[PDB]
Length: 596
View 1 (cartoon, rainbow, N blue to C red):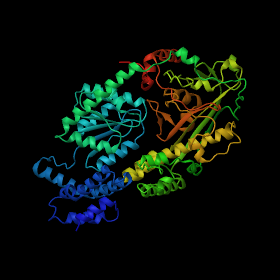
View 2 (view 1 turned 120 degrees about the vertical axis):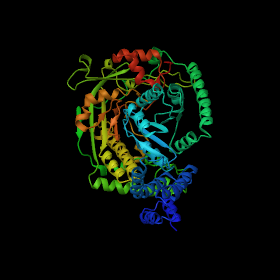
View 3 (view 1 turned 180 degrees about the horizontal axis):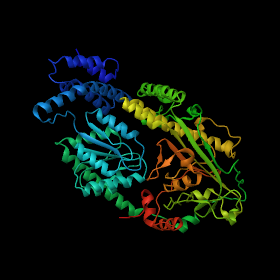
């Protein structure tokens, strides 16, 4: 037969034989009067089987992507004949009928200012495996472009994606723009920075039509199917409304209970050092910026942290094999993990040998002194006590009240730098690294119909950027700064952060202000030296980029700022000499008071 071979090829993801089978199925016009009957018949039968297996957990994401590639290869051969049929019927009858076999049209876009689209690509692949007609608008999509695509393509569902917290305001703007134009299309919210609480509290009330937060693709398919099913279209929305009202009330009643210390009391109870007995900071080997133009990628492969890479493919091993390299011993995901690891290593070797990826970075050191909550950087030849600082990094202090049994201080990043009036010199470093050429390679793989290679190359770009960051931090600790010159640690200990010193990044829990990237880019001249640019939402382009500061102090450790009150917001606005509204815009997720 040919039906059972098409099904087997789709389910097992066999690339070799689907072209001839599809051709012979087309030639069997007795079974299929039109080429569409091939598509709605066995082809979507196998795709539905794959989607049902993925939803039930019996089939994993890499196998699903292989099946999607096989299906795409089949429909690519069948497209010319469908186009011929449509043209012939348009000439003969003057019209083209509503002959679409998909379950619905779904628009996927990444909101303005965000460049991360691996999750969006995975969601699109999984939705396509469920016979959805996915429109992928790409990264940094303007809102008006999203509604233009929805209106022109007659989209049934619009899905927004975002990875950084400035994107949440863009999603809210999109929601209120659909509300202003009275669009009733359901809206889905996805991404790493997104949460169910933020959606129901901030995004959902602005838009009357259903707004649903989707954690991943396996739930996005359920949400889309339940929204497009007219028997469950309204009851599902009623349940969503009930649960979102419940969590809205819970959030607005939790806002009353939480206690925050006054900023002065938090400052008094802040972290402290004995600078008269702790060892003095070590001056770096140079002051200024050193630029890396073409880093050795083979030196970065041994530093790659593979657990976040397996998490991208949703290969989450069970206890005790929850991570690399023990994940290969898992009976459930071990085989697929091994296959994905082997393909990743093969393509990594190919890309490094072919010089298709380039790594660039800049690292800098400047003398730095702390003034309460701020760190002021100075020139090498200037006296800190009698010179105007060249740049300032404004820290945020914890205000949320800690448990009465706890003795932890209220941390700030300026507590790890010696104060200006203590008479002790101190220094601060910063870096920015990236992996280039990922966009072109991903575009080339997608143009060939190979979304598996595109997803893996995006994942490998992120892995190489993180490996470059880790290796550069190891070099700084031992060679470029030499405050840990005798240190010798393996990759596992670096992954465990057992060394001394931290490399906090702007926008992260230690400093959730993304405007700290502007000072770094102006000071270290990162754009001109390395080509890494900041978008209008201060995201790093390319998406495989890492940046941050360097704190060499022994006691320095990672911490979460948490929630801040109005007094700290006004103090921060006064220090930065900016409007309080801008401070609330950039620090929105960490505001602890009702701005509504």
